[PDB]
Amino acid sequence: YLMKILTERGYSFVTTAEREIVRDIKEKLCYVALDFENEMATAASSSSLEKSYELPDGQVITIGNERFRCPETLFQPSFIGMESAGIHETTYNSIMKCDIDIRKDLYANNVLSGGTTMYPGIADRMQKEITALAPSTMKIKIIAPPERKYSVWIGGSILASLSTFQQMWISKQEYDEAGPSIVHRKCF
Amino acid sequence: DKLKEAETRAEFAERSVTKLEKSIDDLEDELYAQKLKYKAISEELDHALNDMTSI
Image (cartoon, rainbow over all chains, first blue to last red; front, side, top):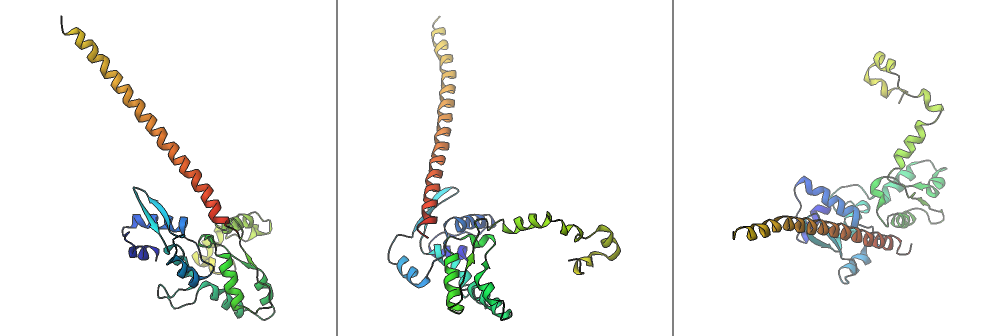
């Protein structure tokens, strides 16, 4: 979507080699706005958000309101035409599907992970949206460890070091006896 | 005869030219490396300012 909206300013990236350049630009410049409407109004009038970047052959580009419009898709998937709601409402819907007794604990113990949740300014937008959706009295906490990118691998390393985990592995004998469909069994 | 006073300076010139070219090239390379380092320092400072920016 960023590569598609960058054509509105003059720069065109098409070949698959340049998708890495667009990815780097997204990683380096994009940020998630706390409130979308007022920020969009400001960015179209003032000039304090327009930031410059250097392509790998020179030819510096200047991105304006595209900084916070590309990551806005996560909270509003109508940009790409997808039907579902944003990630701020999918979380609440998955919470409400749970039983009525464990909604408070999930409210107070929301956890974030993944590389794409590394955008500067997502933990506050998520908090605001969830507060808007969830009942007002409950306390809402969004856990955002500094090491979000490697959280999954750190968890895997911790899991592989446990003593009680030593009998959960799929023995090669079991595969030879039952075939590749052994994974679907109680041996996950 | 008259050839040798010219040949001597002619050969004096070649190695000097090569050495000057090598020196200027290496100095330019160092200059570009330092430029990249300086830009990186500016990037680190500005990234800190942009990430914190009050929270």
